[PDB]
Image: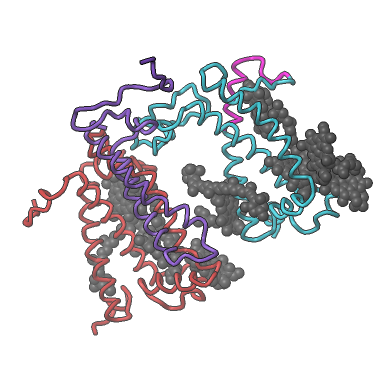
Chain colours: A purple, B cyan, C red
Amino acid sequence: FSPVPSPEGTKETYWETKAPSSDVLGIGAGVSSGNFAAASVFAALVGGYCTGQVIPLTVEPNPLFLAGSFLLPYSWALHVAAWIQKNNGK
Amino acid sequence: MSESVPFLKKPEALDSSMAGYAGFDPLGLSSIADIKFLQESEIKHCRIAMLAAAGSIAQDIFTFPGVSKVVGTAKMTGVHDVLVKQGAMGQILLWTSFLEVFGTIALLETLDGKRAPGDFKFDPLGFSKNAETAKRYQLSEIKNGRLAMLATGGMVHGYFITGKGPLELLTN
Amino acid sequence: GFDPLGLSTLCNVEWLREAEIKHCRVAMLAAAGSIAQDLYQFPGVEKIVGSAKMTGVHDKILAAASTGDYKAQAMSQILFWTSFLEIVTLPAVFETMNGGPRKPGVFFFDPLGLGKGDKMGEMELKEIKNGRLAMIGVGGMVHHYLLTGKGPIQFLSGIP
Ligand code: CLA
Ligand code: CLA
Ligand code: CLA
Ligand SMILES: CC1=C(C#C/C(C)=C/C=C/C(C)=C/C=C/C=C(C)/C=C/C=C(\C)C#CC2=C(C)C[C@@H](O)CC2(C)C)C(C)(C)C[C@H](O)C1
Ligand SMILES: CC1=C(C#C/C(C)=C/C=C/C(C)=C/C=C/C=C(C)/C=C/C=C(C)/C=C/C2=C(C)CCCC2(C)C)C(C)(C)C[C@H](O)C1
């Protein structure tokens, strides 16, 4: 009804292809699919290991293991980015 | 292809002109972040690291008047804990925070394409008035700064094993 | 032309080729290392390891490292440096698969340039055959240790 503002750098992200354009990856638009796939596997193993090392949680835990356990959900987004880049020829 | 790493491809973001270029970016991190931000970040890490390695050596060489009576034994990172009880660190923190506030404004101006990475125009003595000798001092700053990051990490970690401190650990 | 079970149809030939060369080189080091470990012992190691043979050394140094021993962190250090090397040379094996210039196994590592000097039409096959033997020989060495406490030289010397 009036112009709706969006921040500078807003681009068109609607896709009807097999995979979205690499622009949907933001700052990761230039990373290759091999690098996302290897980072995804790495993050999944390190995140699962760190998660496993602190499943009995105690009042004093190792702080690095806590931070490293956040790599398991991050790996899901990494392998989705690997599928997007492999189907974009990157 | 890349110079430093012959099997790997030349980094896209990196350029020959960018001081301290060896074509070294195997993981392609320069593609992820803005290259000027990484350049400013490397230059800043270089200068802090240079000061810290020189300080580590100097702390083994001598001690300013009265410091022996606040801290007796602690040499590298132990001194920081005693000084935070006093105002010594808080003071450095406050003034460096103030200097970094204008560093933040400088970063914003750089990221819009106007200022150059690490260029704060701080050249009181006449050391860069040639623009060929200037290029040599820029590259020397980056190489000495990179060496200093590795050194500062090396010295602090050696203190973590032994507690000796850098030069005394060299002696024994 | 040896592939009776057709396992190159079940994976990319480039990935398999680099994996084969890596297995061959690592096993070269393992087989040569076990024979050298019996023949020569680096100084000081007899107090940390005693007289343990190839696989026993891994478990015994990591047992000592499992206490807080400063003089037993060899395994972690080798693991660290090999992991660092595999992390930074990791994009190479994906560049080869993507159609890149570099062939499987070539990191251009020729300091002495012995391969560069003469035409390298045979040194490649020399490495591949020697490494294939190195893998099988490592297999031999480890399982024979797992049955009899003898090492390379001890087991070869007699015949139980
Ligand atoms: C990252 C840098 C860093 C940090 C955090 C510290 C921190 C400290 N040092 Mg170390 N030190 C440093 C650098 C550093 N110093 C340098 C560069 C030297 C000289 C080579 C020394 C030499 C030194 C000795 C000999 C001793 C300390 C001591 C101390 C402690 C007491 C605080 C004090 O009086 O320091 C004061 C430190 C200085 C005045 C040196 C600072 C010099 C740099 C070059 C400041 C330059 C500012 C710059 C020119 C402005 C640029 C402006 C531009 C950005 C526009 C504290 C732990 C004492 C201690 O507890 O040790 C046991 C002690 O005895 N320091
Ligand atoms: C998969 C290979 C492998 C593994 C896991 C081990 C593991 C071990 N060895 Mg064995 N060893 C190996 C290979 C291996 N070694 C090789 C290749 C040799 C030389 C023939 C030896 C000779 C050897 C001796 C003599 C001793 C050990 C010992 C040990 C233990 C402590 C670490 C140590 O000091 O090693 C020392 C190992 C070396 C110095 C060999 C390093 C050879 C490098 C890898 C050659 C690299 C060349 C090339 C230029 C690099 C290319 C880089 C490129 C990829 C970029 C540890 C269980 C010690 C022990 O506890 O035994 C009881 C001991 O006394 N090893
Ligand atoms: C039989 C051993 C053997 C042979 C013939 C080769 C041959 C080759 N390698 Mg490989 N390599 C090997 C072992 C070997 N490698 C091992 C074990 C490693 C792991 C450290 C490597 C790591 C490696 C990398 C990372 C790269 C190569 C490359 C190459 C090629 C060019 C380099 C060259 O000509 O060097 C010839 C190498 C030798 C003749 C090996 C020297 C063996 C000496 C004579 C003795 C070994 C001593 C050892 C410590 C054990 C002693 C015995 C013990 C029982 C006492 C060529 C096809 C490069 C490539 O493919 O492209 C250019 C490359 O980038 N290799
Ligand atoms: C690459 C390169 C470089 C390099 C390098 C390096 C590190 C080169 C290293 C090459 C190596 C380490 C070769 C080792 C091969 C071992 C073999 C073939 C063993 C087979 C064992 C068998 C068959 C057995 C057995 C049996 C015995 C005796 C024991 C029994 O209990 C068991 C059993 C009965 C089974 C350099 C620096 C030169 C530069 C150059 O520019 C590039
Ligand atoms: C915690 C704490 C404090 C503190 C503190 C401080 C000052 C902490 C500083 C920590 C630093 C600077 C650590 C840096 C470590 C460097 C590393 C790991 C580089 C390794 C190089 C590698 C892996 C490869 C290198 C490579 C090689 C060999 C081959 C190729 C070249 C290269 C790529 C270079 C206090 C003061 C608050 C006190 C408090 O009570 C305790």
Q: Whole-percent x and y of residue A16?
A: 20, 27
Left/right of residue C132 with respect to residue B94 in the rendered view: left
Residue A29 or B137: which is nearer the viewer? A29
Q: Which residue: 30% across, 26% down?
A: A13
Q: Whole-percent x and y of residue A41?
A: 32, 50
Q: Which residue: 86% across, 54% down?
A: B69
Query: In the current view of this chain or complex, which residue is farthest to the front?
Result: A1
Q: Quadrant of residue A20?
A: top left
Q: Which residue: 43% across, 20% down?
A: A8
Could you tell me which quadrant the C terminus of chain C lies in? bottom left
Q: Read off the magenta span.
A: B126-142
Q: Is residue C106 above or below residue B105?
A: below
Q: Is residue C81 above or below residue C111?
A: below
Q: Is residue B101 above or below residue B78?
A: above
Can residue B65 be seen here? The reply is no
Can residue A65 be seen here? The reply is yes
Residue B134 or A50: which is nearer the viewer? A50
Query: In the current view of this chain or complex, which residue is farthest to the bottom?
Result: C160
Q: Is C125 within the magenta? A: no
Residue A31 or C69: which is nearer the viewer? A31
Left/right of residue C17 with respect to residue B84 in the rendered view: left
**What number of labels is visible?**
0
Q: Whole-percent x and y of residue C23?
A: 26, 56
Residue C96 or A44: which is nearer the viewer? A44
Left/right of residue A15 with respect to residue B75 in the rendered view: left
Left/right of residue B88 with respect to residue A16 in the rendered view: right
Q: Is B131 within the magenta? A: yes
